[PDB]
Image (cartoon, coloured by chain):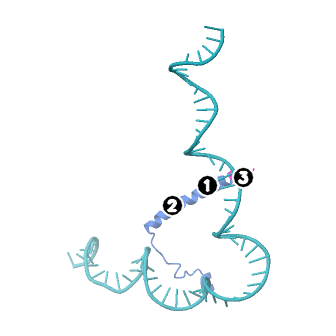
Chain colours: A blue, B cyan
Amino acid sequence: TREKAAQGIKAFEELLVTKWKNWEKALLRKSVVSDRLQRLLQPKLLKLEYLHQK
DNA sequence: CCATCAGTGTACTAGGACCCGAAAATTGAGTTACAGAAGTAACTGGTATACTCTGGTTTCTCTTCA
């Protein structure tokens, strides 16, 4: 099994494809938006907390 | 006439909740220790909203000088 995996022989569950449902196409958008908000907020939130600590 | 091009008649998926039972885990009582923390169960002040005469007031005729 390890030697087979080393040769890059895809197991059955790796070649297993499933269609992108519509609610997933919505969750993705909402989640990317939320993650970008968090990533942009974290620096400024930390700066604000540091100013408060000083 | 051999190209092309919807429909069709199905088992075979794809999500999509949902259920059925089993097995493991817990709860619960019983004891007896142990220390300390919750968790009510109790008496005992403390200060305000009505409250009840009361002290003053107010004309209104009169009192007392003047």
Label 2, secondary structure: give it: helix
Distance (Cα) linking label 2 and label 3: 30 Å
Q: Which mark is residue A11?
A: none
Label 3, residues with CA under 10 Å away: few <14, some 14-19, many ≥20:
few
Residue A20's spot in the image, x, y percent? 45, 69
Residue occupying the point 64% across, 56% down: A42
- Write down the region rendered in magenta: A48-54
Q: Earlier in the sequence, mark 1 or mark 3?
A: 1
Q: Nearer the viewer, residue A26 or A13?
A: A26
Q: Earlier in the sequence, mark 2 or mark 1?
A: 2
**Three-letter amino acid code of the residue under disc 1:** Leu
Q: Earlier in the sequence, mark 2 or mark 3?
A: 2
Q: Which mark is residue A30?
A: 2
Question: Would you say the magenta stretch is mainly helix, strand or loop?
Answer: helix
**Three-letter amino acid code of the residue under disc 2:** Lys
Residue occupying the point 44% across, 69% down: A21
**Three-letter amino acid code of the residue under disc 3:** Tyr
The residue carrying mark 1 is A40
Residue A26's spot in the image, x, y percent? 47, 63
Label 1, secondary structure: give it: helix
Q: Nearer the viewer, residue B56 or B13?
A: B56
Residue B6's spot in the image, x, y percent? 27, 71
Circles 1 and 3 in contact, beta carbons < 8 Å: no
Determine the chain carrying the residue at label 2.
A
Q: Nearer the viewer, residue A7 or B47?
A: B47
* Residue A50 appears left or right of B19: right
Q: Which mark is residue A50?
A: 3
> From what the image shows, is residue A22 above or below residue B2?
above
